[PDB]
Image (cartoon, coloured by chain):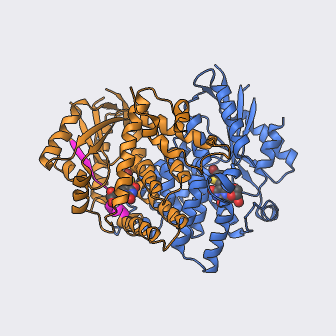
Chain colours: A orange, B blue
């Protein structure tokens, strides 16, 4: 069968991502803005930022913020969820690629990365973050995740330039979110280096120290038994997290440059990403139509 | 290679499902109960109490529809968390379909929290079909040998039992009973529909035994203004979800059990249906013990 290349450009918002991918037998699946602002619900992004603002002003409580916050993360990952779902069966085993799919963000941003950041923000229960993790679909072969690198003040400047409507410059949420992708990038090398959280978990009391991995966020008092132990339910959700992330291929793009440069770099990492065969002759065309119809309908 | 026999007992609450499964188990056979301790304490505080009060608040006109949806959606993520973790942990051992070396008697399948309960809440107006389809996209891949025993039981006889089998924080809500009763009937019809060659897209225009009418399946829940494009066709985002709703269920093995009989009767009834069920091999020979302990542990920690 012919081969495919799936590339998910991911990282914190405000790093110039959509811009540089649009500057790129290659389809680009955008961010489903229409689905957030209109299809799934009314102005999901506004809701997120507003709510946290009410929590920051104490106009509402950590728990009401959690439910609203929780209910929104659902609307945000839905389009990505279904795409991976319908896409999954066509992807074959790892292997010029007959089709290159550039996606704007992977599902883990919705089922892991943003949820965690909001936890880090006192707006999402760690119990909920782990519920989402538990739902992270299996990791198809050839899943290349590009995460971005960019100096803080530079990223603050950028965050400032363009924001979806309803947003708010939230410098904490920036640091919260920059923290997560940083930890996530660390977890992957850890898992890949042979690290076992169960074996290293006691330390929280050639590879990253589990203190610099995503595992360190779940030493959360609400996840532990009166004697300090993690409840098994939760220990298992970390076996899923471990399971899902270890197979991903993470590629770093330095965003501290010009779109032309970022673009030129993005295409550059491509030389080492992993391709896979498709399942049917007609997989490529079906995939091509899905990615174009996804774009057409949800990209504003 | 050893085989495994997985059996998920689901259906509307208040039919006596938990009892009989225990009964049956009291006769290489491990149970996986409902994770009440997670619902009452671990994941959140009193989730079931939260659910029945919210609906109730909405009905009293004391909150809105968007408050309920936000709360309900939130409550459902908690309710199905344990099922979701269990399924993902077990999945790698589940192998090809093939007496069983191990029999795992589950209490409710992931789809109950990712589909049926959501769908029913939607029918109650405390959930949106967009949220349902979000959950549906999150239903995990249907493992081989997914045998589901649903429970039949006449309504009045159900009402009486429900009135009896309440949960801590539960309210006698017949409306929800009827809703939950309708949703599970559609599930069975749907699985029959999908298996007799049915295709929703083909029969979309139209909105044991013979193939059911698409309008007697779950696909009919999703004919909502919210999901339609001005051109009148389902938006593709949802259409693609319904594609997964059909993929997930098409390979399940549904069996129906009659709950209009004594506890020792359902036990024997269910014990009868069990023989015609699909087993499967395990991935590693040592997968059985592991599976045995995950189940016992799930039981020991979240059962109550
Ligand atoms: O889950 C989310 N939650 C969230 O608050 N955001 C924010 C960041 C920015 O302000 C705007 C667009 O990225 O919305 C994004 C996401 C995700 C988008 C796509 C996926 Br997958 S997850
Ligand atoms: O999603 C749910 N929603 C819900 O309202 N219930 C109610 C019904 C009854 O009052 C009680 C116990 O099932 O909880 C149960 C569930 C689930 C339990 C297990 C799974 Br999977 S889904």
In this picture, residue B163 sits left or right of residue B43? right
Q: Position of residue A249 (x, y in %)?
A: 34, 34
Is A45 part of what is drawn in magenta? Answer: no
In front of the other: A176 or B44: A176
Between A181 and B101, which is closer to the camera in this rendering?
A: A181
Residue A296 placement: quadrant: bottom left
Q: On the picture, is B52 further left or further right than B158?
A: left
Would residue A67 be found to the left or right of residue B189 on screen?
A: left
Image quadrant in which you'd find residue A233 = top right
Q: Position of residue A50 (x, y in %)?
A: 40, 69
Say which of A226 and A49 sits in front.
Answer: A226
Ligand 1 quadrant in view? bottom left
Relative horizontal placement of residue A289, taking residue A68 as reference (left or right): left
| Near-viewer residue (A35 or A155) | A155
- At which x and y percent is residue B129? 50, 63
Q: Is residue A34 magenta?
A: yes
Q: Is residue B139 above or below residue B93?
A: below
Given the current orientation, which residue lies at the most extreme front position?
Answer: A205
Q: Residue at x 70, y 43 (%)?
A: B301
Question: Residue at coordinates 60% horizontally, 75% vertically from top-left?
Answer: B58
Q: Which residues are magenta?
A: A26-36
């Amino acid at each position: 069968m012919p081969t495919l290349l799936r590339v998910y450009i991911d990282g914190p918002h405000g790093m110039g991502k959509t811009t540089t991918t649009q500057l790129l037998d290659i389809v680009y699946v955008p961010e489903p803005m229409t689905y957030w602002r209109v299809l799934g619900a009314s102005e999901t992004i506004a809701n997120i930022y507003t709510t946290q603002h009410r929590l920051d002003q104490g106009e509402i409580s950590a728990g009401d913020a959690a439910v609203v916050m929780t209910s929104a993360q659902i609307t945000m990952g839905m389009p990505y969820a279904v795409t991976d779902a319908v896409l999954a069966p066509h992807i074959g085993g790892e292997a010029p690629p007959a089709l290159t799919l550039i996606f704007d963000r992977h599902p883990i941003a919705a089922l892991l990365c943003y949820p965690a950041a909001r936890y880090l923000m006192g707006s999402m229960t760690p119990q909920a973050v782990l519920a989402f993790v538990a739902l992270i679909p299996p990791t198809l072969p050839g899943t290349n995740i590009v995460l971005g690198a960019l100096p803080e003040d530079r990223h603050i400047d950028r965050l400032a330039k363009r924001q979806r409507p309803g947003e708010r410059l939230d410098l904490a949420m920036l640091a919260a979110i920059r923290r997560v992708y940083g930890l996530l990038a660390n977890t992957v090398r850890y898992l890949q280096c042979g690290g076992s959280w169960r074996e290293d978990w006691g330390q929280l009391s050639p590879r990253p120290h589990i203190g610099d991995t995503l595992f360190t966020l779940f030493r959360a008092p609400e996840l532990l038994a009166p004697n300090g132990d993690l409840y098994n339910v939760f220990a298992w959700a970390l076996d899923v997290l471990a399971k899902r992330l270890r197979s991903m291929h993470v590629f770093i793009l330095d965003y501290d440059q010009s779109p032309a440069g970022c673009r030129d770099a993005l295409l550059q990492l491509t030389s080492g990403m992993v391709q896979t065969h498709v399942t049917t002759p007609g997989s490529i065309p079906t995939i091509c139509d899905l990615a174009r119809t996804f774009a057409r309908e949800m990209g504003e």
